[PDB]
Amino acid sequence: GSSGSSGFDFKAGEEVLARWTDCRYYPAKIEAINKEGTFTVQFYDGVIRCLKRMHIKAMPEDAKGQDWIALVKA
Image 1: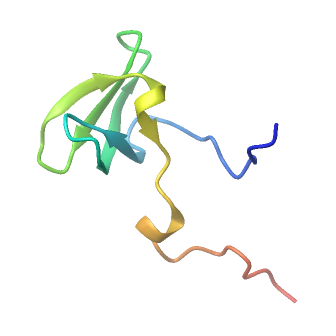
Image 2: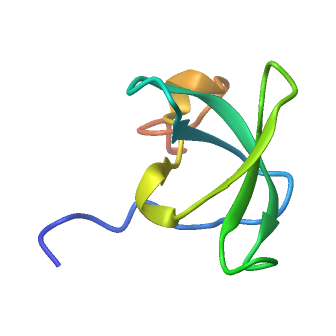
């Protein structure tokens, strides 16, 4: 526990962040899941590589927009 539960949904075509040859994170998307014991991903440049879950993260709501966090009905 002690780390939240706000989301964990991952699928082929989902947009994500990943660590690259450069230590900074960058906008990417999932191309495949467990297909080669790894997560295949594609970057905005068009390049495709395979990584572990330990090098990939879900992007924030600020990277997508039009969210509903703390905007419940009344």
